[PDB]
Image 1: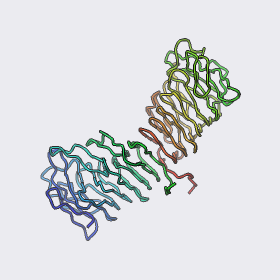
Image 2: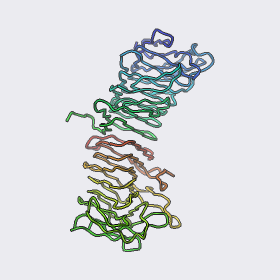
Image 3: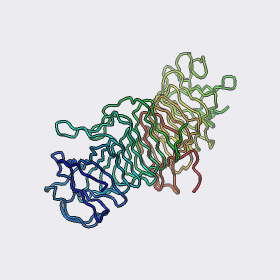
Image 4: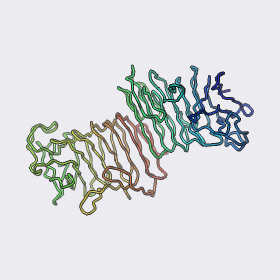
Length: 242
Length: 242
């Protein structure tokens, strides 16, 4: 019951295997190739969650045998955008798998995202955005972390993916092992393009320091904190107030 | 007496103000704009060191009034390459200033480099290379950290520069605040171009993990560890053996 779709036209169908692994029959992709899914709640438990991007029945890693997603009509999604539209933060405590055609995946939740033993399967690029998507004339234009001080937290059990990983938030607090083909961590109050080019940056009211403890196992690591007055702190397992 | 030039044709003239701040009259730049200085020892103490890249007398920050460097004939260096050719590691315990025309600066020492409260003044780009420069037909071709397991250590008093910073070594162990316009840390056993493009990478005999504790205050941070079996560990103030 961790994932609760919005009642409107962008809410996908969600069902759970024996109360466990959640399967999301994502909405039909639009002309941009984006399946834009909106949620009142988005949380993944230990048993994980599957985005059904399959045109034929088959074998998912987390859920076993699944039928095709009948919301797709001949064309799978290129980008699976999951947007939390409520005030509820997200907790990711297990794996998220794209079943079927490999895609990019984005979770946006301006209220905060916590990962702890989460990961992304069959994703070419996975992005966790503590912010909102920006739409203009019905097209995705990018993302915004403006006027937001909430946290992308990564816990001691870490985050694993074979694909590219973007960590996009006002601030990050990571305490575990991050594994990805490449890690990009862009922090501060910013607007971004769809590709996470930084388009603009605000000066925050107070410091937005990010903290990293643990390890990073990746081909490339890039970190950019655009907040004035702020930095990137390489922490031990606690950061006590001074 | 921390800096001891080689006796040959690339050894600069070195003198100390009252036994304190060391002033290096760097050798004449070659047709590539490189002043290629070779040393039996290169160490900077608390009072700092000055590379004299000045065509006229003037005011250095660390040493006060200095005469022009008569080794330059009308043309200042573009790149000040400082190569330790002995087995002695380098310790940088104070600031290093380019007096006169802003230049790029490189210290190469395959035996190890330790920074602790060091920094770089009036440098557009400063590179610390635990490795050797590569020359072919008399021209600088790049740098090599191949077949080397030594350490670029950065201590609790940190490293500060207004320019770009490259940290190039088999492994890095940093325990302080690193301040730079941009930080690039490329670790593992590699060959590099003159611009620190990674041209090739070796598989080391044993793990080459790098460790970072402290903080990074920069516009851009990039870290690449090319060593198989190895990672980037975000440490607390100790990393005890497990």
